[PDB]
Image (cartoon, rainbow, N blue to C red):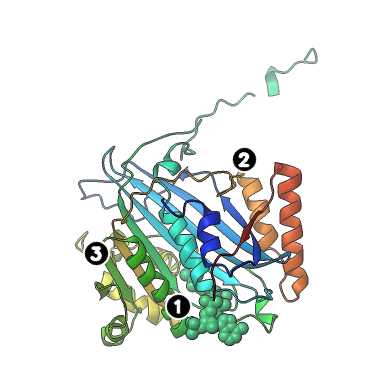
Amino acid sequence: MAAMMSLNDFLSSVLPVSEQFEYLSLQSIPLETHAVVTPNKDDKRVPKSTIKTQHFFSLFHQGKVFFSLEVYVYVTLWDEADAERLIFVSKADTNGYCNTRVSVRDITKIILEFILSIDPNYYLQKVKPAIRSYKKISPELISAASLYLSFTCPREILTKICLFTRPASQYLFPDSSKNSKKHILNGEELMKWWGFILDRLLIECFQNDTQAKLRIPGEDPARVRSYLRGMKYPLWQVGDIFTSKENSLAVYNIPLFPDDPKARFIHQLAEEDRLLKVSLSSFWIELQERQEFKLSVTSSVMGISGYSLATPSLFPSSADVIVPKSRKQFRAIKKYITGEEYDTEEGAIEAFTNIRDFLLLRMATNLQSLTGKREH
Ligand SMILES: CC(=O)SCCNC(=O)CCNC(=O)[C@H](O)C(C)(C)COP(=O)(O)OP(=O)(O)OC[C@H]1O[C@@H](n2cnc3c(N)ncnc32)[C@H](O)[C@@H]1OP(=O)(O)O
């Protein structure tokens, strides 16, 4: 954290010179959650705790939202000296209501790099417990006469990035594909768009001994390998970061993320009682063969696993992030973006005006403004 420290610093460095933008950086209160990967009974170490935090970002220009990004950070604790973090990139989207040229690719990369700079201890200082104790008072006692957990871990811990590329008309902006200015990448372009972002993350932010993995489920590895040849990070391989013998059973290896085609298919296997039957190999085949084919669309899975070049030591300021007091408040603010109709620019205007009004009135806070620094 030497040149660029703030989320303001990071966004500004990739946004066009002298142009003005605003951002929403919204964050849930960290909470205890189920392990990312289902534990096996016959394993010698099960996580002490798994802590999950959502970062939701929205970028604005000229009083209109135009981009949003939803990311989940999981800190998995095995002991005091033994921990891992994983950044799951869940949904990125645009609505086409921006009248200036920006690189959404670079905005997306730079956001993840801000996130990579956060000390995992930031999420561990105040954590909502998975099980809360309550004493409930029966109304019978009224007459006519009347806790957060905390943890620590090392700053420099094993860092994972996971994402599933799959194009759609929209993920965060309903009916935005009705906007003729919205630019939708096809599956192949989108896989390349994310592979470019990850390649730069590896080169700018990770040590040279880092695992970098790409698979295209149900497809022969010969296609994957050819593409990887153009990467600048020297250690990309075909496959994933889940591999190895927790047994070959998919359920004890596949991570389970919100709204992810994985989890969705593990859940179908659960309903079919086949969790103790399907190997990782059959998994990737049936994922495509039985579930993902209906989308008629090129999809890929990408994983990174390794150590950051610089020790993450940022605790985001109130400028960097807004953490609502409440889960209801988090949800109401996010829904001003995600519950809007974007078939006209009026949806992009209304999202901005509702968000800024909510923040000002309920939380005495503004959207942050940015002046771009990148020349052409
Ligand atoms: C993990 C996941 O979330 S996967 C799901 C991803 N999200 C979606 O599929 C939802 C729909 N897609 C989108 O919203 C968009 O297509 C995104 C966010 C994926 C990318 O948005 P874009 O604005 O295309 O991104 P960006 O600014 O980086 O430009 C990408 C390329 O498209 C070009 N481009 C951008 N806008 C336009 C346009 N209106 N017309 C023509 N070309 C354009 C750029 O020149 C660039 O070209 P290059 O890659 O050859 O340099």
Circle 3 Cα neighbour tier, 10 Å, few/some/many (<14 / 14–19 / ≥20): some
Q: Earlier in the sequence, mark 2 or mark 1?
A: 1
Mark 2 against mark 1, which lies toward the viewer? Answer: 1
Marker disc for residue 283? none
Image position, residue 123 (x, y; %)? 45, 43
Classify mark 1 as within 8 Å of ligand 1 or not, answering yes or no: yes
Whether residue 294 can be seen here: no
Residue at image x 76%, y 15%? 143
**Callout 2 secondary element:** loop
**Callout 1 secondary element:** helix
The residue under label 2 is 325
Marker disc for residue 193? 1
Circle 2 Cα neighbour tier, 10 Å, few/some/many (<14 / 14–19 / ≥20): few
Instruction: Name which residue type carries label 1.
Output: Trp
Q: Is residue 17 left or right of residue 132?
A: right
In the current view of this chain or complex, which residue is farthest to the right?
A: 144
Residue contact at pointers 3 and 1, CB within 8 angstroms: no
- Figure quadrant of residue 20: bottom right
Instruction: Name which residue type carries label 2.
Output: Lys
Residue at image x 29%, y 37%? 80
Q: CA distance from mark 2 to mark 1?
A: 36 Å
Q: Earlier in the sequence, mark 2 or mark 3?
A: 3
Q: CA distance from mark 2 to mark 3?
A: 40 Å
The residue under label 3 is 208
Image position, residue 201 (x, y; %)? 38, 66
